[PDB]
Image: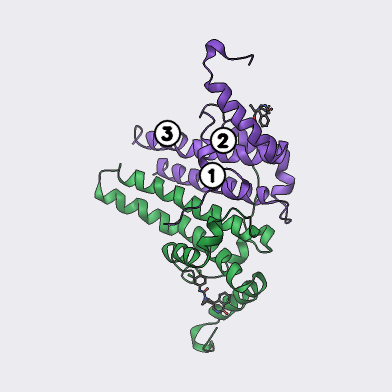
Chain colours: A purple, B green
Amino acid sequence: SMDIDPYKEFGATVELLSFLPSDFFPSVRDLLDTAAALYRDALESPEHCSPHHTALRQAILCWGDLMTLATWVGTNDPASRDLVVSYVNTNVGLKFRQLLWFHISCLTFGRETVLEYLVSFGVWIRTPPAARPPN
Amino acid sequence: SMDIDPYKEFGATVELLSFLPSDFFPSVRDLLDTAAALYRDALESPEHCSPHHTALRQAILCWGDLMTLATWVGTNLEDPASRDLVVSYVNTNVGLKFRQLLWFHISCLTFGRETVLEYLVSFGVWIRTPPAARPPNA
Ligand SMILES: CC(C)CN(C(=O)Nc1ccc(F)c(Cl)c1)[C@H](C)c1c[nH]c(=O)c2ccccc12
Ligand SMILES: CC(C)CN(C(=O)Nc1ccc(F)c(Cl)c1)[C@H](C)c1c[nH]c(=O)c2ccccc12
């Protein structure tokens, strides 16, 4: 195979994004709604806009396909077609939660802010509750 | 919902790429291999390179996710009848989608966006002429 990192050209890495815990990311539904509310305009645009836009467009579309597949599985066993769709939110979901979050956040607050923040938050959430400064 | 066209910002549309028949596109395997042979250096890079490079990166990765899911489903299905109907679905539907998109991007990097689009119309016209009357080389 090849070894491409989605975050590489954006000055980050898969390792770095996994530094944030899995329960810090919004939902996929919420992230898609937010992208729409903040960016539908530019996302549906024919202008490139920015590399972030180009990526996010593909991320959204890709989540599209993944679901259409989990849909088409459950529309083709109540404990099996239900546990297939469960795997998606388990695994890929985290993947997209990260990736959507990264791109929306980078468009909304700046790439640099999103990286400063991500490290601070990982350090901070790993400090045990006992001694952790104010939320 | 949102209505995003992967090709829109690249001066094409889903409609237009559906103009070429489904058997004109190389396989996904062949398209990935070609992306690697020609572009692995740039694809692996930290530079943006071009919007195409950005887009192709995501396409490849996405295909990656789709397979890891189809795999996982097949190694969890049990019946050999039903592993046969899962892999059918992916070639039928998502494959064509990715065959188009991988192709569009690779070719655009290789021969230039305008060429790719001239050619695509020429071919769609030419292949739709019935065989009887159609010239030799598209
Ligand atoms: C209100 C948000 C700033 C909260 N938040 C977060 O990213 N949430 C969020 C970010 C992007 C989203 F699309 C959605 Cl749906 C949610 C995190 C926790 C955050 C907190 N504080 C920050 O200073 C910050 C800066 C950049 C990026 C994120 C943050
Ligand atoms: C050698 C290619 C120019 C052949 N080809 C094609 O698309 N093949 C191809 C294109 C992209 C690929 F990644 C792979 Cl693996 C194969 C088609 C038939 C083609 C033919 N003639 C053309 O003049 C042409 C121009 C632009 C794009 C494609 C073409």
- Mark-to-mark CA distance, 2 and 3: 14 Å
Q: Do tag 3 and tag 1 residues touch (Cβ < 8 Å)? A: no
From the image, which quarter does the N terminus of chain A lie in? bottom left
| Secondary structure found at label 2 | helix
Does residue A87 sit above or below B106 in this rendering?
above
| Secondary structure found at label 1 | helix
Residue type marked 2: Val
Q: Is mark 2 within 8 Å of ligand 1?
A: no
Q: Do tag 1 and tag 2 residues touch (Cβ < 8 Å)? A: yes
> According to the image, label 3 marks what residue?
A86
Residue A35 appears in the figure: no
Query: Residue sitting at 65 percent across and 58 percent down?
Result: B51
- Mark 2 surroundings: few (<14), some (14-19) or many (≥20) residues within 10 A: some
> According to the image, label 2 marks what residue?
A28
Q: Earlier in the sequence, mark 3 or mark 1?
A: 1
Q: Is residue A66 left or right of residue B121?
A: left
> According to the image, label 1 marks what residue?
A63
- Mark-to-mark CA distance, 1 and 2: 9 Å
Percent coordinates x, y for residue A111 in the rendering? 68, 40
